[PDB]
Length: 42
Length: 53
Ligand SMILES: *[C@@H]1O[C@H](CO)[C@@H](O)[C@H](O)[C@H]1NC(C)=O
Ligand SMILES: *[C@@H]1O[C@H](CO)[C@@H](O)[C@H](O)[C@H]1NC(C)=O
Ligand SMILES: *[C@@H]1O[C@H](CO)[C@@H](O)[C@H](O)[C@H]1NC(C)=O
Image 1 (cartoon, chains in turn cyan, green):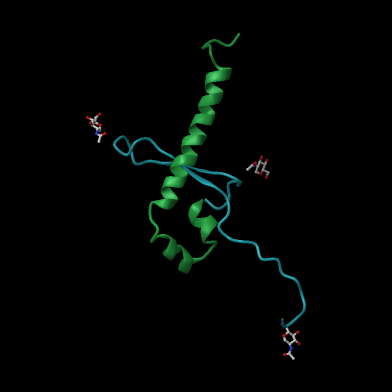
Image 2: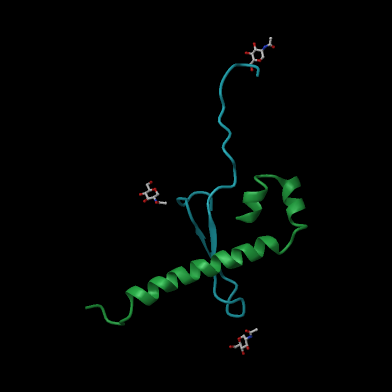
């Protein structure tokens, strides 16, 4: 509204996240598969 | 994602959706059950044999 320009609003919180883990009775170490992304956020 | 689909990027709405409880979990339980059997459907059709000829 102040200076005239058109700003696209892109929703945050994007891309799928998966949890690759053995049973918690085995180990608590987990691998996290991030769909729809490159290795950046982490 | 049934928290994201219903309430987009919203804390006030997501707090209201958490009052609905297991609804979000039971939908993904059925979608995962599909996602598992669709890999099983492909497993039953294309691999009937252990050896690659
Ligand atoms: C309002 O702010 C914009 C910059 O965002 C500026 O270009 C404009 O001149 C301002 N208008 C007035 C009169 O405050
Ligand atoms: C955890 O693993 C141990 C050793 O294999 C087994 O004896 C036990 O039944 C398991 N417990 C659970 C909760 O899976
Ligand atoms: C990620 O980007 C690199 C180039 O910077 C590309 O070579 C790689 O295939 C990309 N990986 C994904 C997420 O497809």
